[PDB]
Image (tube, rainbow, N blue to C red; front, side, top):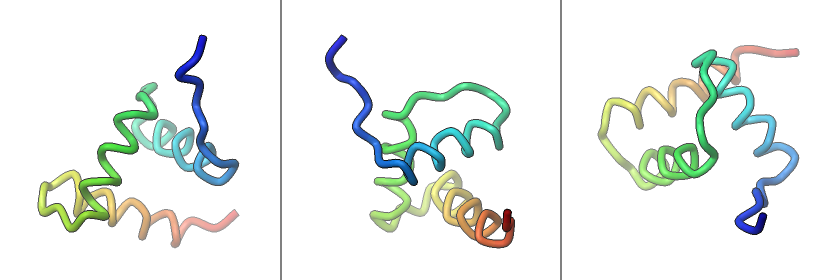
Length: 62
């Protein structure tokens, strides 16, 4: 066991939701790495795209 996920309720939804977007199961660690770099001001294509994904999400209401 151990190394259990400690993501918040909102974060859990975000990770599962990102998976839904890629329709493929991804790890939480990877998600943290992606946001970490993006939020850290990364220029990588995945970073700007990630920020956009948040923007698209903002557009997508219940």
